[PDB]
Amino acid sequence: PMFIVNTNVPRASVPDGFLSELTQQLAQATGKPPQYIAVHVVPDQLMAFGGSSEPCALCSLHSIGKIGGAQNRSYSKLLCGLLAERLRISPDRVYINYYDMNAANVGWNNSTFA
Amino acid sequence: PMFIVNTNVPRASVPDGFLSELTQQLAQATGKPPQYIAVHVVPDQLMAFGGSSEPCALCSLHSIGKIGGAQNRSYSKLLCGLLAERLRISPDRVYINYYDMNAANVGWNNSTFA
Amino acid sequence: PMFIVNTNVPRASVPDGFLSELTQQLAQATGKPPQYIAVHVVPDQLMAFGGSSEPCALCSLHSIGKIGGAQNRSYSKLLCGLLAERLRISPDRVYINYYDMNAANVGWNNSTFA
Ligand SMILES: *C(=S)NCCCC[S@@](C)=O
Ligand SMILES: *C(=S)NCCCC[S@@](C)=O
Ligand SMILES: [Cl-]
Ligand SMILES: [Cl-]
Ligand SMILES: [Cl-]
Ligand SMILES: [Cl-]
Ligand SMILES: [Cl-]
Ligand SMILES: [Cl-]
Ligand SMILES: [Cl-]
Ligand code: NA
Ligand code: NA
Ligand code: NA
Ligand code: NA
Image (cartoon, rainbow over all chains, first blue to last red; front, side):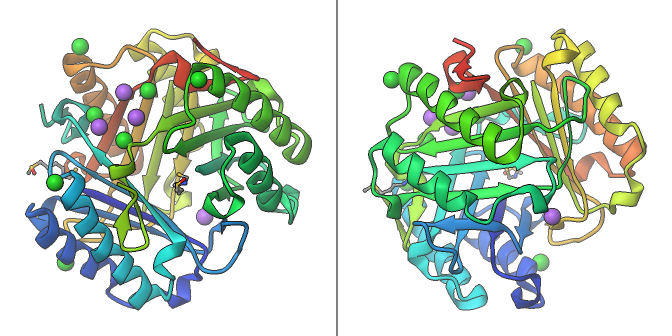
């Protein structure tokens, strides 16, 4: 699983341990070992949501399987909750693109998971 | 709709109103209210296009529907025009990846659009 | 072809001419002329892989065709090799998402490749 968050919120407002919490909570959410979870946080971005420059975020969650209608709603409640509580970003100013990746299309360790 | 632009042009060369201009133009192009549109511009990037470092841009346009052969050809003209005038990027040094997203794979406000 | 690398390694550790090496190596691996190849390297990122902040990378390779089981394994060996040699990133701390793009979904110079 790979979770990426792009936001206009300043780096200083990202709480210590945020990447660790994301790793831990995504491991529990996806059911995959935390060892394989990758997290990427990109603050101080130049972005807008609805024409407003107030706090917002554009994210991505890639995973080989464990992606679906019900699961994605669950991931959204989890992730929007964290962005709201930890980064003070309103849930309605966050978009998360979910990708169900084929094992053959994910490279790792000089090979792929296929 | 979500539009992201990654470019090597300096932050100082990105007009302060560019995000709003993109939002408004994309609202008209997609026929969606500006409120639903998110924009993200990433300047000062380390990039090369065709083995050259002159101004260039790698972009992404995500949308739940409103994506297709004909529509994409139209978006390219709209976006290349904006990047050409406001960021000084030659249109033949711009790539735009279009993504037609399923509502179930787009998270927002603690849920998804499905 | 479009190759993007997001890594936590410092900018200073990115060798001069690294972009050129990626361009030429990708031209060889994909068979496409270098004039159409785009490369993007993003260092100094706030990332974690397996919860650890040791050197790691999240990448993407977009291409109209030339994507597949065997081909992707080959690309991974090539790209992980370059990241290990040039950026000192362990191959088991690198993920590469491969995307086989439909020509109609890749915009360039006021149109698409369809
Ligand atoms: C997230 S995309 N992890 C990469 C794929 C892991 C394969 S099995 C160990 O889930
Ligand atoms: C762009 S990806 N907007 C996402 C969906 C916006 C709401 S629907 C009701 O158009
Ligand atoms: Cl599901
Ligand atoms: Cl895939
Ligand atoms: Cl269409
Ligand atoms: Cl989708
Ligand atoms: Cl952890
Ligand atoms: Cl193949
Ligand atoms: Cl596609
Ligand atoms: Na998919
Ligand atoms: Na799609
Ligand atoms: Na940056
Ligand atoms: Na594809």
